[PDB]
Image (cartoon, helix red, strand yellow):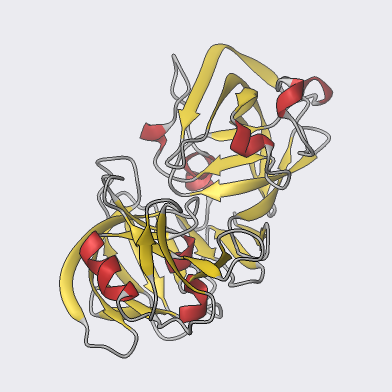
Amino acid sequence: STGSATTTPIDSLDDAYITPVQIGTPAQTLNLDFDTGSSDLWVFSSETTASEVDGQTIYTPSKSTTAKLLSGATWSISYGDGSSSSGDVYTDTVSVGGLTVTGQAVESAKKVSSSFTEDSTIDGLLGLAFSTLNTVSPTQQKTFFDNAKASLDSPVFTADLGYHAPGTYNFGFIDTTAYTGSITYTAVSTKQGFWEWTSTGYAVGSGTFKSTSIDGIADTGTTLLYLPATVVSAYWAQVSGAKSSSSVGGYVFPCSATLPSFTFGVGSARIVIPGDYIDFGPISTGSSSCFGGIQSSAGIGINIFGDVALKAAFVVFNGATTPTLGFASK
């Protein structure tokens, strides 16, 4: 089997991407944030504290004839941005782009943190990291990909995120028309539960490539590109007037600037992030100070190849017995 679904930016800055997901019988369609940096499929629901729901579409298990309470199971998760959610668990039928899993753990939120409430466009998350990170207790549950894998034509999914435009998540096949040149594959460590890999280096604008190993995660659920302070300083040094602002919480730059590109290495291959992908706009409405899309990972404890990086590539998440990641230009 295969599936294919369009993923759409939630706003004009590509802060995140939503993909429609069919849950239950009859289908209830919710728009979920596909997140290769976590492993829980959770949704706003009829069980969510009413004051914490503000415009989201909810899953109502009582209206699904295939929903079953997973007795005794609870979940609770926190993300890198300090947001969180928790609740109980149903199993139900879940379909993405024509690909159906029966008995998928659908984690129903009883509580969500303010950032989720305040974002009307995201109805929940669909985790695509390794199932070892799944938070369901006392019986850990499998991700949608993990459940689908054996049925897929090939045990892979691909992320093709757009810049200020829709893109595609495919399951079970590689669309050879969706990228240019070749896909370069690189090793993955699953030791921390993430799609963790090692970039071979970077360049800033038209500058020379620096060969250096950069361990990080391919994370569709993180907006920006978070790299070591040395790398980030080298990037922003090429932008006149750019500075790290403690008050804003990162590098900012004059909105009048033309940003240089940023290249990262995948083996001997190179992925180029155009300068425009690194502009996240005014820090506040009407400001001429703009927020940068490349930020320091110092104090995160890990480097994160988030959407800024991934949207410059066609990315293969290869879930073979020994997982690997593939990157192609597009």
Residue placed furthest toward the top: 72
Q: Position of residue 162 (x, y in %)?
A: 59, 70
Where residue 88 sits: x, y (%)?
60, 18
Asked if one can make out residue 264 in the rendered structure from this viewpoint, the answer is no
With 53 as the anchor, is 232 left or right in this view? left
Please name whichever residue, 4 or 236, is drawn nearer the observer in this view of the structure: 236
Vertical placement of 3 versus 147: above or below?
A: below
Relative to 215, residue 177 above or below:
below
Residue 133 appearing in the image: yes
Instruction: Give the quarter of the image for residue 11.
Output: bottom right
The percent coordinates of residue 199 (x first, y second) are: 25, 66
Residue at (43, 53) in percent of width and height: 219
Side of 66 where 319 appears, left or right: left
The quarter of the image holding the N terminus is bottom right
Which residue is at 61% across, 58% downward? Answer: 284
Against 293, residue 300 (above or below) is above
Q: x, y percentage for residue 23?
A: 72, 37
Tag count in the figure? 0
- The answer to which of 165 and 185 lies nearer the viewer is 165
Looking at the image, the residue that sits furthest to the bottom is 206
* Image side of residue 316 versus residue 87, left or right: left
Q: From the viewer's perspective, tell me whether residue 126 is left or right of residue 11.
A: left
Location of residue 144 by image quarter: top right
Residue at figure coordinates x 36%, y 53% from the top left: 320
Seen in the picture, residue 191 relative to 174 is either above or below; the reply is: above
> Residue at the location (36% across, 33% down)?
132
Q: Nearer the viewer, residue 33 or 70?
A: 33
